[PDB]
Image (cartoon, rainbow, N blue to C red; front, side, top):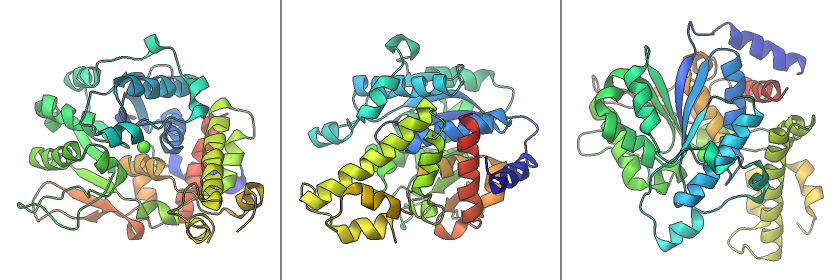
Length: 355
Ligand SMILES: [Ca+2]
């Protein structure tokens, strides 16, 4: 670690809960770095007693694709010394031919990290249901992917969820328009909502009907707290296979995008877009990489917003619910009050986890 990377951690450790929060995670890894960065910081947050990641249900793609994502997730948890995490593939959800193409994106970098098929399960949220029935304390639900399985969990176990879930924290989007009853509803444009829009609608609505507090972190929250390439270069620096996966995934993705834009293989985007997005022409990528200053970490910030100790340190969520209704909070650009502490905590946790 670095000195300032210690003081923020030291500071976080002041806010350790009495018991770690048992956590149910809904995730779609290996189409970008986001989800695996989250597993990485979760490792350190588990080490320091903020959470315990008991169950992970994986979505995005058809049944076999979800199993591949599940095997990848498993492989990462194994390499993070998190051997107890129970990973299962989610259930089928509606897919056009177009979605079947797009939802099947699976980075080559992840192929070699895949655990054996028998290391992961096929029965979705069943174990989560069984856990909800037998847990002595309330659990958190963290949603960093499409909402097919999170919604199914509420549909199947609404009785249990009402009594046994403390909150549902979601990397999603809020329609500026409330529904007929003034309930918050998902934005059709936010990636995790659009994966299965009807499941997202059903999750946002049913959480409020059941009185489960909802916390929605939207993409603009990540902008202030975006990290440089050194976040990635740093975690890979000691040869940790998860750190190396992450750095390679982020760098290769950005490289493919620059080169495709440049050659016009990706005609709808231009150099000007790339520069506004990642920085602040005819160049090769090794000349562009050092200029990159902004890399967004949506899913990790979402996990940070889900734990009371981390959230108090970084955010002031804005209430969105009608008076006396089931609570709904928004974390957007203005609600991230210590973005530089956020950036530092993210780096500290990630580095610590890979030691
Ligand atoms: Ca994700």
